[PDB]
Image: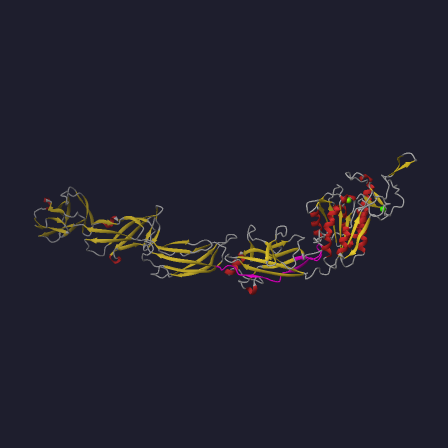
């Protein structure tokens, strides 16, 4: 009648992105019924078999079936009995009826000729010939125990007065008989129901204990089935079956379209012949919409419960056939593996209990739009206690759509959120309750929830990024190289759905100040739910290393720049005179992977791991192979040509470049001997070749051997010394500078005797030690 609908979404505190939806409903009537008076007719088997003492009572005694139902209706000392139940409401009135058949028909006639009686005229298998008895009453196999009455006391007395017929039952005998003529009871019920209030709820409750062994004829005389003379053999001839089905059908045709409900209880049903089944069929044929059920009871307790069930279906607590439904918006989803804890809670006067599986079921359809429909279907018959709170509770989490939205990666459209605020996302697309009030699926109203709740997703992430600049040897060594002025960094978001990764998702630029080695900056509003990586510039002179120092779910990136090492070649000039000299130094460079190197590095270019440095005064006698790969192996050697005149020693000539190295080529100019020929007594001449022998012993006292560079007339020439003797030809006023002679060697100059042809030969510095540049002169006088 009256219903209260409320729905909210409550944040589960200290669980990120988890909420609880609560959809409650509360029933309210006010009084007893919404002025829907009941007209209830009880039809009771009063057959002989219904006095069978074979029923276990609540108190542990076996009593008779009559005795049992005498208690189930009236009530064991004001115990809640069917009578009381129904007539609790003063608008409600009830009629009671008892049925039991008498044998109006004969089996087989015999002939008593004042002597003997043997079978004369058979009737039992009627080929349309049965004869009955005389004076038998038609329509006499049932009586109204109680006409329409709202007087519970009178009814309790009437039940108390219910009793089974006495003697073997012939149609002559008055009152009901001891047979089962179910047709009889229903006939009378139909009559009573015709006098029922035609704006009440007409309900009939049938009760039987065995199969119907009797059928009324068209005239109302009772035909008994003599095939069932043995109670242990329920067997019937064809024509009897026909009449029974027809009678049942006819009764149903008149009753069912007037009834609002029909209920049958087969107490202690024994006969394999099942005819309450047949009744249900015909009833449904003539009214498929009415509640139509058959119960099975074997003891007094089972009878009470089954009776009560009917008094709970016609006489309501409240509302039934209940179903609570929520369609979730795109912005929420259910926890996997039924972790949402779908539960319906009942509020009993403050206190509360969880409805069981037998009270409520849960369903998960995916809807036509493409959203999820949570459906809380209650047991069809479950009635909501008047003024109790039945609340559906379950957990949901933010969808990716929501997580995207709060980061600002998805656009709120129309009615996705309250006032297009991402902190006010709507959790439901729509939600509803369906219920019925009355008997069966009659009223079936659907109210849509008025409330549209809102929630805020978890704060998007702040993904931090640090940039460390390290010098050659590591952190806290000064950087000597040009840094850029800043580096632009870009957060990359790996695409879940396919291949197209977002390489410009967010962006930040980090200032690079010299003399500050650590600087952090942040990417703000990053969406939860994704893996992320970092793009960072390749800075010249440095190596890069990007690493996520955090988690996947909470990234934090660091980028380390470490300056590459470089090799410097210095040349030192011992015996320095000329400053405007150049020297070439070779450097073989084998990179890590033990593979040769290729690239350019300062002003020095590297091919297959070779490189050549030309050093001179204006270059500060230095050359630098800058920012070579870490751990590059190097090996130095001065070029052959440049080792002329000089003894060349070396420092750091080979190693690995893990720090900045300096290799140093020192050069010691070696002594030189110069010999000059001067002539006296002549002026200019062709006869001028004078042959002059030089003897040199090393410092080791050892005769010199091999070739040395001698310049004559600005023309480098090889001079061969053999056993410390060489010879030269000099012209008037010519010199020869023999270069590269060993330090501390000793020399002698003399003139070949044939070349001294009538010449006074004089000498200056004729012998000497070569501790530096020495010079000799030979003079001639003709
Ligand atoms: Ca009769
Ligand atoms: Mg019976």
* Residue 101, picture quadrant: top right
Residue 263: in sight, yes or no? yes
* Residue 192, picture quadrant: bottom right
Q: Is residue 420 left or right of residue 752?
A: right
Color encoding of the figure: secondary structure
- Residue 752 position in % (x across, y down): 11, 45
- Residue 404 position in % (x across, y down): 52, 58
Q: Is residue 709 left or right of residue 278?
A: left
Q: Residue furthest front?
A: 77
Depth check: 572 or 487 in front? 487
- Residue 767 position in % (x across, y down): 10, 48
Residue at 68% from the left image edge and 45% from the top image edge: 60
The answer to if 129 sits in the magenta stretch is no
Number of numbered tags placed on the structure image: 0
| Main secondary structure along the magenta-highlighted residues | loop
The answer to if 439 sits in the magenta stretch is yes
Depth check: 232 or 217 in front? 232
Residue 676: in sight, yes or no? no
Q: Is residue 349 left or right of residue 203?
A: left
Residue at 86% from the left image edge and 43% from the top image edge: 105
Q: In this view, does 398 lie to the left or right of 221?
A: left
- Residue 620 position in % (x across, y down): 25, 57
Quarter of the image with the N terminus in it: bottom right
Q: Give the range drawn in magenta.
A: 434-460
Q: Which residue lies furthest to the bottom in this view?
A: 419
């Amino acid at each position: 009648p009256q219903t209260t609908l409320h729905k909210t979404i409550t944040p589960i505190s200290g669980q990120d992105d988890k909420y609880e939806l609560s959809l409650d409903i509360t029933s309210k009537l006010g009084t007893e019924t919404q002025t829907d008076p009941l007209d209830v007719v009880l039809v009771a088997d009063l057959s002989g078999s219904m006095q069978n003492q074979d029923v276990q009572s609540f108190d542990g005694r076996t009593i008779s079936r009559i005795d049992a139902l005498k208690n189930t209706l009236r009530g064991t000392n004001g115990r809640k009995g069917l009578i009381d139940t129904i007539l609790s409401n003063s608008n409600n009135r009830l009629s009671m009826v008892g049925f039991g058949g008498k044998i109006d028909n004969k089996k087989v006639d015999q002939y008593w000729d004042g002597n003997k009686w043997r079978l004369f005229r058979p009737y039992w298998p009627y080929e349309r010939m049965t004869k009955y008895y005389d004076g038998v009453s038609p329509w006499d196999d049932a009586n109204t125990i109680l006409g329409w009455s709202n007087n519970a006391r009178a009814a309790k007395t009437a039940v108390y007065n219910m009793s089974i017929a006495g003697g073997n039952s012939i149609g002559t005998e008055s009152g009901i008989g001891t047979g089962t003529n179910i047709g009889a009871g229903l006939t009378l019920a139909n009559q009573l129901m015709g006098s029922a209030r035609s704006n009440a709820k007409k309900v009939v409750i049938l009760l039987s204990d065995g199969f119907a062994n009797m059928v009324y004829d068209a005239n109302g005389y009772t035909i008994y089935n003599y095939n069932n003379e043995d109670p242990n053999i329920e067997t019937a001839p064809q024509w009897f079956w026909d009449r029974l089905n027809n009678n049942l059908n006819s009764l149903s045709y008149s009753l069912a379209p007037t009834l609002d409900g029909f209920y049958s209880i087969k107490f202690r049903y024994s006969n394999n012949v099942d005819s309450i089944t047949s009744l249900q069929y015909y009833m449904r044929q003539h009214n498929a919409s009415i509640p139509n059920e058959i119960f099975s009871a074997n003891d007094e307790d089972q009878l009470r419960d089954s009776f009560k069930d009917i008094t709970d279906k016609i006489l309501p607590l409240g509302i039934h056939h209940v179903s609570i439904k929520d369609v979730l918006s795109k912005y929420v989803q259910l926890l996997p593996n039924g972790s949402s804890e779908f539960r319906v809670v009942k509020e009993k006067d403050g206190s509360s209990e969880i409805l069981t599986e037998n009270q409520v079921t849960f369903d998960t359809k995916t809807t036509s739009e493409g959203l999820v429909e949570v459906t809380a279907k209650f047991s069809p018959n479950y009635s909501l206690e008047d003024g109790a709170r039945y609340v559906l509770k379950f957990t949901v989490t933010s969808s990716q759509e929501a997580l995207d939205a709060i980061a600002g990666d998805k656009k709120l459209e129309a009615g996705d959120a309250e006032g297009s605020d991402v902190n006010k996302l709507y959790s439901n697309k729509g939600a509803s309750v369906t219920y019925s009030y009355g008997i069966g699926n009659s009223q079936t109203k659907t109210k849509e929830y008025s409330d549209n709740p809102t929630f805020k997703p978890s704060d998007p992430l702040t993904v931090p990024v640090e940039v460390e600049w390290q010098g050659v040897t590591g952190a806290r060594t000064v950087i000597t190289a040009d840094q850029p002025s800043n580096v632009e960094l870009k957060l990359v978001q790996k695409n879940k759905n396919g291949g197209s990764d977002n390489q410009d998702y967010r962006k930040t630029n980090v200032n690079v100040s010299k003399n500050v080695s650590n600087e952090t900056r942040n990417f703000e509003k990053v969406a939860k739910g994704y893996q992320y990586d970092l793009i960072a510039p390749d800075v010249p002179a440095f190596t890069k290393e990007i690493k996520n120092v955090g988690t996947e779910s909470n990234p934090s990136f660091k980028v380390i720049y470490k300056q590459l090492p470089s090799l410097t070649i210095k040349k030192v000039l011992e015996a320095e005179n000329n400053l405007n000299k150049e020297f070439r130094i070779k450097v073989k460079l084998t990179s890590p992977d033990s593979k040769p190197l290729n690239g350019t590095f300062g002003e020095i270019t590297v091919v297959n791991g070779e490189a050549e440095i030309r050093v001179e005064k204006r270059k500060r006698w230095r050359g630098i192979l800058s920012y070579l790969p870490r751990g590059t192996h190097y090996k130095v050697e001065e070029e052959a040509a440049s080792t002329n005149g000089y003894h060349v020693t070396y420092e750091n000539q080979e190693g690995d470049l893990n720090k900045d190295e300096t290799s140093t080529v020192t050069n010691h100019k070696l002594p030189s001997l110069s010999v000059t020929k001067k002539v006296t007594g002549v002026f200019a001449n062709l006869l001028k070749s004078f042959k002059i022998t030089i003897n040199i012993r090393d410092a080791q006292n050892s005769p010199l051997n091999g070739t040395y560079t001698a310049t004559v007339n600005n023309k480098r020439t090889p001079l061969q010394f053999t056993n410390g003797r060489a010879s030269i030809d000099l012209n008037k006023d010519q010199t020869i500078k023999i270069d590269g002679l060993p330090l501390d060697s000793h020399y002698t100059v003399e003139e070949e005797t044939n070349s001294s042809r009538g010449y006074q030969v004089s000498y200056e510095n004729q012998e000497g030690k070569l501790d530096g540049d020495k010079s000799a002169t030979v003079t001639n006088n003709k």
